[PDB]
Length: 127
Image 1 (cartoon, rainbow, N blue to C red):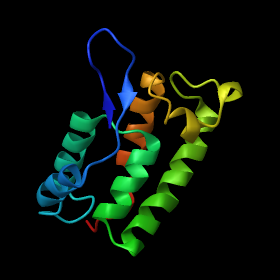
Image 2 (image 1 turned 60 degrees about the horizontal axis):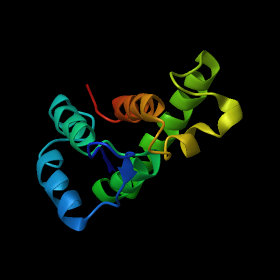
Image 3 (image 1 turned 90 degrees about the vertical axis):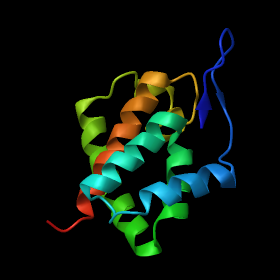
């Protein structure tokens, strides 16, 4: 999670199991990628402002190996497309996207990365 205390640089803290369990008890009420799941996983991203690494750690905790694999494959396609477009706050000469999305100072880029990660869940549900 990325924290925003007043007057000092933003800082990363690791997930705590109580964070993860509280997220699971909400998100896992619904099928992955369903509208209900999307509301609750978006709320978790809002509350915790996670880095790219945090998001993979969260995916691997919440989802089965198969579901995580489907998500990761879709995300890697979305990232390729986004890099071709260009991404807010992202200078590719200053580090790979995923690395920069772990630098707490790169807020704009992290927030965009979060939206890509959230959008990747659209590959999961049945209509």
